[PDB]
């Protein structure tokens, strides 16, 4: 079962009272079973002189100090590669529409921005930094991190930027502490994660008065002994973003791939429904 | 990991050097012939000295120069060793005695010496500069790594 | 960086009634865990404490246990790493009196405290001091939940930047943290934090009874 | 060349090389008691022999 | 804003010295008795170096232990306040520094038999308090003095020197300005011999110059070696007088 | 499918190879079985140290994924229980991408799988079976399934695929699918048409591979 | 200087028979046998260290001015256990290497009555534990020069009922005995290695001048008077004072300094430099006019 | 009834000593600390005092264990799925399930997984097997079997990965515990053919282990059900 | 013991059996949440399971693994 | 740092925990050990000091200056702590670094007015600490050295006008001439708690057996923050009665001026 809490850690959590200190653009808390996932989205302003992605920093807590494990390295890249290849975030959606700030001599403070100019252009660009914390891990956790990141990306607000008259001394370019616009991403490309496994069990079963497949791998027992696995990122439109297959313990029949596609599609329907409500 | 050499080898090679002889049948002042092969792309070069095989790849990308040097571009040389050249080398061991020496020899021979015109790597002063990178790949080892790398 | 994905290095970051909620034993990855949420006025703090141990150290000849505490930034990057180490050193100076070390020879207890969030509202025409009593509350709960023997319940309070931790029903002190604020608040802060201690203590004891039940 | 011979029994065990003793003397009966694994009840007998 | 030259027609340099003058040398033994087995405080010009020799002693990890020879370690701490302009970052991991540390080790591995202290470790800690040219040569002299103070056996002295070259003639013992102005050669000299433990050239140097530059350095290093013997012997005489 | 490979090119390694498909050139080396580090030791099985080096720049998280997928293929191939408490170092140095590395890593992964297998063969390490990997892509308008696509074809692709199968019985029986890495979106009819034509060209490749192996190695034997 | 004595100095980092120099030649007589501190090439004999030339018979050597203490066979040393491994301890003595001990080189509680057990080698930590101090005699020497210790005596064993302090090993020489009884009912143990143990005088010491189950107990004497404790502190300070003046520590020197230090009311007055220097100076001059 | 049934960590239960009046004679109740309790020192008004204090949150249970009478009461605290069980630690005489990590010629080292309780039930020691934090133990060649203690072929007794039920003679050093499979109920319990590559094998003879699946037979040291 | 009474008694009295109010601002509801499961029927619609029922699945397996020897 | 046996530690506790407390040395509960201080030996820096303890503990402090815009540079005094042969990252290093920076904040225990040059520019002070050797908590050792260094520091003198809002002249400094940095550096005292006794300047062996410890700052003739309780060791740490805390503050409050008086000599 999956239960989430979106926009709880963001600065845009409350409409009336906005956090002046918090720099989180979008957030998501997720817990599937025992494993808990906490995603926070931050940003940056970059000058610019087809689709892009975000830069995730996953921290899986196992209770050991030291550098980043090979797990955290691969996941950070796998999240970055999948988003980049699933075409979720276009480079045009990250374009910064700036503005101007003209100040009266204590008479007034004026800020002006134009919608029309940006459409004509159709130029600072936004960059989305992500950090994903994982608590209480119990198995393959890439899917959990992906789903939490997807829900977090569904709700991201990009604050507008502007500069008070300045000369190319030191000049500080600033964003607005209030005004912001919602991030526009392709919902048609939005996918969700799920894992599957293939194994054979010898043991006989008693009776009282041919391959088998397991969905959503958890527990050490399944992660350790099941060497034939399938990973899917599926979309509600029914377009599929990616597919991970590796058989190391048993043969992978085409009939099992089809079930996974059906299983993955069903998961996408379930996840999609949750987002709507 | 420490390589094992027989006492018999250590006595044989040492005695052979006193008789002006060596295993690969060379002289004392002789340098093994160097073979240079260029790839399809520019900056792709393969240097071979006997069994010693090294490969270098030159690349560059638009970057911004340091505040201290607004007229100079960026230039770095990478020589990370790998177990491919032999199991004697630890993967990513960039602090070992021989590794740091080799890294410093190349740097003082190319970087510090100003073999490359870093001033000509500047596009717009204090704003945009080219960043040339020299990546050396030690494919296999039969000695002479420093000589192979400089070439 | 070849370890993580820091993105473009030529870019720049963004430039612009006491209430308690206690929950323990919600993490199956460690031996003991705790969740502490406090909301006062416009200021609220939520942190998670994870305990791993006691686990045997090979070759260790120590006749007692060894405690290690580390604070982490869960979301908002506010507190300096240098300051996090300072509090950690302060926290370990407290629980080394609280934890019965004689029970775990040749062993070590690692304590991870994740400061996932703190929300600060400041009006316009120290800082980490207020979080300290909540960190002590979280750890003492996580240790007691883990099964680690504690000589007494550790608790604290924050009064005008002056933090002081109590055990044995406020009769003695296991930690003292004073930054800035004002002088001659010695007697006052000791009395105000003692009330916060007793309040935090009973809720901590009730917490274990509830979840344990 | 220096070392001097003396009867073994009188001297307390000595670290120094110069002192020489024909036999070690702490538990001569007992040393050999360990070897044949002789019980301490027979110990009195063993010492006499 | 200013400008400056190197060598004037009057035979004078930017600091006032002539072509062949050693800077002020002060040497100091047994400066940190309660911190190390051997210690030396070096003052060669404005250069200020603390050198500590800790050992031979038990290794902290049995994994790193040689049963045939002692383990020799050297760590150079170039402080952030060594120069006029304080460096923001630490210099410890810097590839330039790793090469220096490596270089120094290679030098003294052949100068101490290091066969008479098996299953031990010799740790050499160095702190550079102030820097003003020829820091490598000063590092060499500091280690040699400190090692001797520790009563650690070695075959001979190793004296370090700095060489500055302009036009036809090199300048002995270069400071930072001269080092900035012209290429320098750092020489490691063993005892009173002509044998070099360390030959270090990091900038461009005409090939004609080196033979003569080496000749100047070796002669100057001999003077430095003589001074060091005087420095320790003189101290001993002074210490004996103090005792009396 | 006009690939070209050489075996035993490195001197200071137990086994090595150089696989080339189109532009994509990868050189691989294998040392083992040898003494493992304590943190690498496996009580009963062989420990694999897998390293992937990029053609340009240093190894990043990208190559960390190439190492992971390459691990999924090589692990079940090797009879690991023959070497308990032992290590096998496997290093891949990609010499030429043969593709836009900023967008794809398809051809580099397949070439690494084929090269690693060849290096394992050269090193004389116990293998349960044989293996071959090919890159596949799908066109934007034509939607055709192109096996071994060029770099230019990848630019205009809708999906990219890495397929590595496990073969037994003289390279005629597909024991299992070691790795299938599909990025993009799919239709069922295209997939099986791809698998049918793909199996044919793979079988032709093994036959060619067998020829190459015999021709080079036979002069060495007696 | 009522609370703290702070000596200050400005503009300076710090304050203040043939001659021997490096590269120096000692002799050119090839008949000589070259010893420590020297090295040779044909007829020439050179010095390897800074020190004084020593000629004993035909053996030419150079005695260094400084260096590590060296273990001679039969020395009475005091050491603190560094590590416990296998069937031995490695005990810090203060040399180049840790002291070596063999389970068969120590004496078990109950002794002769006691029977050999194979569980002793697995329970060595119940006898000697890291940090413990003890008396020991250098039984033998290893090839490199390391020492093998033994405590096969009532005289040797675990130390208690006192306090530890150390002086440079050069200030303590070999003697007939290193355990001494002093006024104030305290006993000193002057290890040749420079490690010194000051404790309350036990019955053992008294017997010499004229329970085997608790020879490894960490417990001290439950009844130790303040007068003994304040005596230990005083003996400690005067020993440090003798060490500060490079004065060789002997039993006569210690007691002499202890009684001479009685001039100063508070014991803490003995930690100041001028007090230490004068106390040592008074001892040398006392030996002058008495000699 | 005098002492609270359930005590949280830090709650006072009962003083050091106790006594009551019955049958015209004083009965002395001696309170001794147990699992979950810790005898500590508390002073009030300048007065020193020792009392039994619980260290774990649990219900409290007492049990008697051993002219003028004489008594001894054991005071302890029991918690009250997830199981931790730290108090449980390998001690001389206990039975322990282990797994073979490596085989040498003169001995066989393993790692401790679970420990048998006392009246079957076991106490599982949770630790990371890919780190080395797990307790390691060593089974000597002389401790393999009582039959022919001198010459024993270790290859024909144990095998890497095989599960071995043994009894610990002594703690040994920090590295290795001492393990003996001399008796009948001790030996290889669970094992597979070819170091775990084949199928499951079962114990028939004490010195022979067979597999009723592939018909494979490997020589092991088997125990008795 | 009487000293115990005055101090012990005083200590016992102080707590006052004060009432406790339960709330979670954000994290508390989601983190301590026990494990849950759902099943997708042929309709494709998710289906919930009773908490008691889920446990029953656990206790039934334990009896079928222990007692039901073959 | 120091390693002691169980027997030695108990004896030390008996010696020091006694009602008439006796130092193993023989000191009184307020007596410091003799120290030596050197100043003005680094000409390259604006100020410098070197403190030597009786146990060989040695610390070197350097003071360097830099002109900064105080409108963008919040902290005008940065303390940096280091130890050769020691990693920078270590818990002890960062804690002391964080602590010292609070002790010498711009608007807490330091007259930052004396660092101001113009309306827009001020002097940033870099206090670099180098601990060569130490056998106990070096916080008080470093504090004495920083004090001595800051009281012998000389900064460049400004020439140009001090109104950047209007005329906006580039900051220029007259050659040769310099102005002594008039400032009041705070001191950091460390205490040891053994039983019910409080000791000033805890020795190594004393700290090992101590039940607890206190870090109390001192400025302008009064107690000031940061005030921190600290575990000198980790094997014998116990809670302490509040009266001990008040005793410690009182103890510092009466013996500090004596220390400052012996330290204020130019």
Image (cartoon, rainbow, N blue to C red):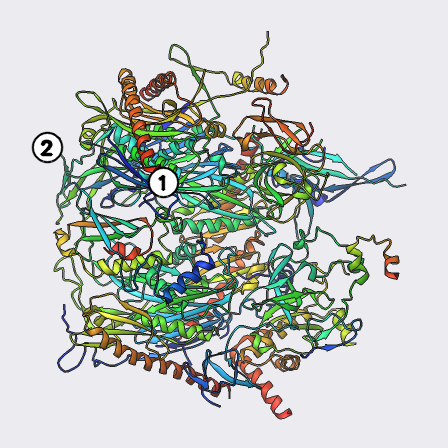
Query: Along the line of sight, which residue is nearer the eye, G226 or H84?
Result: H84
- Quarter of the picture containing the C terminus of chain J is bottom left
Q: Are marks 2 and 1 in contact (CB under 8 Å)?
A: no
Q: Mark 1, residues whose alpha carbon is within 10 Å: few (<14), some, or many (≥20)? A: few
Query: Along the line of sight, which residue is nearer the eye, J182 or F147?
Result: F147
Residue A120: where, in percent of width, then height?
A: 9, 30
| Residue F72: quarter of image | top left
Label 1: which residue?
F220
Q: Tag 1's secondary structure?
A: loop
In this rendering, is residue E168 above or below H10?
Answer: below
Both labels 2 and 1 in a single chain: no
Residue J185: where, in percent of width, then height?
A: 37, 65
Q: Mark 2, residues whose alpha carbon is within 10 Å: few (<14), some, or many (≥20)? A: few
Residue F204: where, in percent of width, then height?
A: 29, 25
Name of the residue lying farthest toward the front: F222
Label 2: which residue?
A121
Q: Is residue J106 left or right of residue C193?
A: left
In this rendering, is residue F38 above or below A271?
Answer: below
Q: Residue at (27%, 77%) from the top-left corner?
A: E217
Q: Is residue A57 left or right of residue J244?
A: left
Q: Chain of mark 2?
A: A
């Amino acid at each position: 079962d999956v239960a989430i809490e979106n926009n709880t850690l963001s600065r845009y959590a409350d409409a009336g009272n906005i956090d002046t200190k918090n720099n989180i653009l979008g957030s998501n808390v997720l817990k599937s079973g025992k494993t808990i996932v906490i995603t926070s989205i931050t940003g940056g302003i970059i000058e610019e002189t087809n689709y892009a992605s975000v830069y995730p920093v996953v921290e899986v807590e196992r209770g050991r100090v030291g550098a980043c494990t090979d797990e955290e390295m691969t996941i950070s890249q796998k999240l970055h590669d999948s988003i980049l290849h699933s075409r979720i975030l276009p480079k045009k959606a990250l374009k910064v529409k700036a503005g101007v700030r003209s100040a009266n001599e204590d008479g007034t403070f004026s800020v002006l921005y134009p919608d029309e100019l940006e459409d004509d252009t159709l130029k600072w660009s936004y960059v989305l930094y992500a950090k994903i914390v994982v608590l209480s891990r119990t198995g393959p956790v890439f899917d959990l991190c992906w789903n939490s990141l997807m829900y977090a990306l569904q709700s991201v607000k990009l604050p507008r930027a502007f500069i008070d008259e300045r000369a190319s001394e030191t000049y500080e370019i600033i964003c607005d502490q209030t005004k912001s616009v919602p991030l526009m991403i392709n919902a048609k490309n939005i996918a969700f994660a799920s894992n599957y496994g293939i194994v054979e069990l010898d043991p006989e079963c008693q009776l009282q008065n041919n391959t088998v497949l397991i969905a959503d791998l958890d527990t050490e027992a399944e992660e350790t002994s099941i060497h034939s696995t399938i990973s899917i990122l599926a979309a509600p439109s029914g377009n599929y973003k990616q597919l991970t297959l590796m058989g190391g313990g048993a043969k992978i029949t085409p009939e099992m791939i089809k079930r996974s596609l059906l299983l993955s599609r069903v998961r996408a329907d379930d996840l999609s429904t949750r987002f709507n409500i | 990991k420490d390589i094992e050499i027989s006492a018999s080898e250590s006595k044989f090679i040492l005695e052979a050097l006193r008789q002006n002889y060596r295993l690969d049948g060379r002289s004392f002042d002789q340098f093994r012939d160097v073979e240079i092969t260029f790839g399809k792309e520019f900056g792709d070069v393969s240097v071979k000295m006997g069994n010693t095989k090294v490969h270098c790849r030159i690349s560059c990308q638009i970057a911004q120069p340091y505040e201290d040097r607004p007229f100079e571009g960026l230039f770095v040389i990478s020589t990370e060793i790998s177990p491919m050249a032999g199991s004697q080398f630890e993967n990513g061991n960039i602090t070992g005695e021989d590794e740091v020496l080799c890294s410093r020899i190349i740097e003082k021979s190319v970087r510090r010496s100003g073999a490359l015109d870093v001033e000509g790597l500047c596009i717009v002063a204090g704003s945009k500069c080219w960043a040339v990178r020299a990546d050396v790949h030690f494919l296999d080892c039969d000695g002479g790594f420093i000589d192979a790398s400089c070439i | 960086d070849r370890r993580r994905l820091l993105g473009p290095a030529a870019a720049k970051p963004m430039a612009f009634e006491q209430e308690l909620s206690l929950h323990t034993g919600f993490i199956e990855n460690c031996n003991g865990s705790a969740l502490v949420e406090a909301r006062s006025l416009g200021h609220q703090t939520s942190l998670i404490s994870a305990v791993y141990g006691p686990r045997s150290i090979r070759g260790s000849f120590t006749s007692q246990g060894t405690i290690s505490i580390q604070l982490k930034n869960g979301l908002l990057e506010k507190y300096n790493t240098n300051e996090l180490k300072e509090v950690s050193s302060f926290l370990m100076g407290i629980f080394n009196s609280v934890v019965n070390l004689s029970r775990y020879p040749k062993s070590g207890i690692d304590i991870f405290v994740y400061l996932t969030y703190d929300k600060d509202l400041t009006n316009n025409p120290s800082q980490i001091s207020s979080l300290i009593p909540h960190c002590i509350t979280s750890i003492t709960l996580a240790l007691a939940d883990a099964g680690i023997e504690l000589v007494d319940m550790a608790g604290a309070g924050e009064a005008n930047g002056t933090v002081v931790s109590f055990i044995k029903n406020g009769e003695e002190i296991v930690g003292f943290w004073k930054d800035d604020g004002d002088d001659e608040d010695l007697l006052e802060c000791l009395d105000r934090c003692k009330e916060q201690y007793n309040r935090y203590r009973d809720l901590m004891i009730s917490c274990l009874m509830n979840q344990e039940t | 060349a220096k070392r001097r011979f003396e009867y073994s029994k009188y001297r307390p065990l000595t670290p120094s090389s110069e002192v020489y003793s024909p036999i070690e003397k702490e538990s001569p009966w007992k040393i050999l008691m360990y070897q044949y694994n002789i019980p301490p009840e027979r110990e009195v007998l063993v010492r006499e022999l | 804003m200013s400008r400056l030259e190197i060598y004037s027609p009057e035979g004078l340099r930017l600091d006032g010295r002539r072509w062949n003058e050693l800077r002020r040398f002060e040497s100091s033994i047994n400066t940190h008795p309660h911190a190390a087995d051997g210690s030396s405080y070096m003052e060669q010009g404005n250069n200020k170096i603390i050198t500590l020799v800790k050992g031979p002693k038990e290794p902290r990890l049995k994994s790193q232990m040689d049963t045939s020879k002692a383990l020799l370690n050297v760590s150079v701490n170039i402080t952030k306040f060594s120069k006029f302009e304080r460096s923001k970052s630490s210099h410890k991991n810097e590839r330039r520094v790793l090469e220096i540390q490596t270089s120094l080790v290679r030098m003294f591995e052949k100068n101490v038999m290091l066969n008479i202290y098996p299953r031990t470790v010799i740790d050499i800690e160095i702190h550079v308090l102030e820097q003003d040219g020829g820091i490598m040569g000063s590092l060499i002299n500091g280690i040699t003095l400190a090692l001797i103070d520790a009563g650690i056996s070695m075959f001979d002295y190793i004296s370090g020197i700095s060489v500055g070259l302009y036009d036809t003639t090199p300048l002995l013992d270069t400071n930072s300005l001269e080092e900035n102005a012209m290429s320098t050669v750092t020489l490691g000299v063993v005892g009173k011999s002509e044998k070099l433990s360390l030959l270090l050239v990091e900038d461009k140097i005409p090939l004609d110059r080196l033979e003569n530059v080496l000749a100047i350095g070796i002669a100057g290093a001999h003077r430095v070696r003589d001074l060091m013997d005087e420095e320790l012997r003189k101290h001993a005489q002074k210490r004996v007088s103090n005792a009396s | 499918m006009s690939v070209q490979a050489e075996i035993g090119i490195l001197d200071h390694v137990d086994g090595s190879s150089e696989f080339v498909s189109q532009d994509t050139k990868v050189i691989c080396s294998v040392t083992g079985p040898i003494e493992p580090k304590a943190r690498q030791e496996l009580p009963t099985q062989l420990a694999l140290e897998i390293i992937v080096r990029p053609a340009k720049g240093v190894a990043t998280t990208r190559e960390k994924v190439l190492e992971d997928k390459l691990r999924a293929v090589l692990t079940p191939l090797i009879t690991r229980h023959c070497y308990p408490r032992q290590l096998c170092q496997i290093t891949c140095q990609i010499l030429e991408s043969g593709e836009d590395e900023a967008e794809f890593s398809l051809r580099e992964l397949s070439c690494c799988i084929n090269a690693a297998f060849l290096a394992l063969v050269d090193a004389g390490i116990a293998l349960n079976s044989m293996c071959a990997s090919i890159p596949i892509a799908i066109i934007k308008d034509t939607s055709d399934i192109i096996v071994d696509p060029t770099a230019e074809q990848l630019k205009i692709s809708l999906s990219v695929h890495t397929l590595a199968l496990e073969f037994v019985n003289g390279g005629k029986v597909v024991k299992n699918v070691l790795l299938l890495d599909s990025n993009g979106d799919f239709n069922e009819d295209q997939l099986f048409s791809l698998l049918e034509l793909g199996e044919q060209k793979c079988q032709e490749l093994v036959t060619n591979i067998r020829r190459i192996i015999q021709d080079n190695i036979s002069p060495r034997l007696v | 200087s009522e609370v703290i004595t702070i000596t200050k100095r400005n503009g300076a980092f710090q304050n203040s028979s043939q001659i021997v120099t490096p590269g120096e030649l000692v002799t050119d007589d090839p008949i000589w046998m070259r010893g420590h501190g020297t090295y040779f090439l044909d007829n020439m004999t050179y010095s390897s260290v800074a020190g004084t030339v020593s000629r004993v018979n035909r053996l030419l050597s150079v005695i260094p001015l400084k260096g590590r203490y060296a273990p001679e066979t039969g020395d009475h040393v005091v050491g603190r256990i560094a590590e416990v491994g296998n069937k031995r301890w490695k005990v810090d003595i203060g040399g180049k290497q840790h002291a070596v001990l063999m389970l068969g080189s120590v004496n078990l509680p109950g002794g002769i009555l006691r029977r050999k057990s194979e569980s002793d080698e697995l329970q060595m930590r119940s006898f000697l534990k890291e940090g413990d101090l003890l008396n020991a005699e250098v039984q033998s020497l290893f090839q490199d020069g390391s020492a093998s210790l033994h405590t096969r005596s009532l005289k040797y064993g675990k130390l208690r009922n006192g306090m530890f302090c150390q002086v440079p090993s050069s200030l303590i020489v070999r003697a007939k005995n290193h355990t001494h009884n002093l006024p104030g009912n305290i006993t000193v143990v002057l290890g040749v290695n420079g490690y010194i143990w000051l404790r309350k005088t036990s019955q053992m010491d008294l017997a010499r001048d004229t329970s085997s189950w608790q020879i490894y107990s960490d417990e001290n004497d439950p009844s130790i008077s303040n007068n003994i404790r304040q005596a230990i502190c005083r003996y400690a300070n005067v020993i440090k004072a003798l060490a500060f003046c490079e004065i060789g520590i002997t039993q006569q020197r210690i007691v002499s300094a202890y009684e001479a230090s009685m001039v100063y009311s508070n014991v803490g007055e003995l930690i100041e430099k001028n007090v230490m220097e004068s106390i040592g100076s008074d001892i040398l001059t006392a030996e002058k006019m008495r000699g | 009834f005098q002492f609270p049934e359930i005590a949280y960590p830090g709650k006072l239960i009962c003083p050091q000593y106790g006594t009551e009046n019955k049958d015209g004679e004083d009965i002395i109740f001696n309170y001794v600390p147990g699992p979950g309790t810790k005898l500590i020192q508390y002073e009030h008004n300048g007065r020193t005092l020792e009392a039994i204090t619980a260290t774990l949150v649990g219900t409290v249970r007492c049990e008697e264990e051993k002219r003028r009478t004489v008594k001894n009461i054991l005071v302890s605290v029991l918690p009250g799925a997830n199981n931790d069980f730290a108090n449980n630690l390998p001690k001389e005489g206990d039975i322990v399930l282990t797994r073979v990590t490596r085989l040498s010629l003169q001995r066989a080292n393993v790692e401790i997984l679970a420990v048998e309780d006392k009246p079957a039930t076991f106490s599982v020691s949770q630790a990371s097997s890919d780190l080395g934090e797990t307790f390691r133990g060593i089974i000597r060649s002389q401790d393999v079997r009582s039959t022919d203690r001198d010459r024993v072929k270790v290859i024909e007794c144990f095998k890497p990965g095989d599960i071995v039920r043994a009894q610990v003679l002594s703690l040994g050093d920090g590295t290795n515990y001492y393990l003996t499979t001399a008796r009948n109920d001790l030996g290889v319990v669970f094992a597979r053919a070819a170091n775990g590559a084949g199928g499951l094998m079962y114990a028939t003879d004490w010195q022979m282990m067979t597999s009723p699946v592939t018909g494979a037979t490997e020589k092991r040291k088997c125990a008795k059900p | 013991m009487e000293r115990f009474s005055v101090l012990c008694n005083s200590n016992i009295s102080k707590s006052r059996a004060k009432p406790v109010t339960n709330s979670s601002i954000l994290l508390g509801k989601i983190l301590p949440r026990e494990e849950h499961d759902i099943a997708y029927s042929k309709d494709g619609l998710p289906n919930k399971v009773k908490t008691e029922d889920i446990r029953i699945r656990a206790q039934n397996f334990k009896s079928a693994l222990a007692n039901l020897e073959d | 740092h120091m390693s002691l046996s169980v027997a030695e530690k108990s004896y030390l506790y008996d010696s020091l925990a006694s009602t008439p407390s006796i130092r193993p040395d023989g000191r009184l509960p307020h007596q410091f050990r003799p120290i030596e201080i050197f100043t003005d030996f680094l000409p390259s820096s604006n100020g410098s000091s070197r403190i030597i303890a009786s146990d060989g503990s040695e610390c070197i402090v350097s003071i360097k200056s830099k002109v900064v815009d105080h409108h963008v540079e919040n902290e005008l005094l940065q303390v940096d702590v280091d130890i050769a042969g020691q990693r920078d990252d270590a818990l002890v290093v960062e804690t002391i670094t964080s602590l010292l920076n609070k002790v010498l904040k711009s608007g807490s225990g330091v007259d930052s007015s004396k660092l101001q040059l113009t309306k827009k520019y001020s002097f940033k002070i870099f206090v670099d600490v180098l601990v060569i050797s130490s056998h106990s908590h070096p916080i008080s050792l470093i504090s004495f050295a920083i004090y001595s260094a800051l009281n012998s520091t000389y900064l460049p003198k400004l020439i140009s006008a001090f109104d950047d809002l209007e005329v906006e002249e580039l900051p220029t400094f007259h050659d040769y001439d310099m102005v002594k940095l008039d400032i009041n550096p705070p001191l950091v005292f460390i205490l040891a708690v053994v039983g019910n006794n409080m000791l000033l300047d805890p020795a190594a062996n004393e700290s090992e057996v101590a039940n607890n410890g206190l870090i109390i700052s001192w400025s302008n003739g009064k107690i000031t923050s940061p005030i921190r309780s600290v575990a000198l060791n980790d094997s014998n740490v116990k809670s302490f009665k509040p009266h001990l805390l008040k005793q410690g503050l009182a103890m510092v409050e009466k013996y500090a001026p004596d220390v400052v008086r012996s330290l204020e000599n130019l």
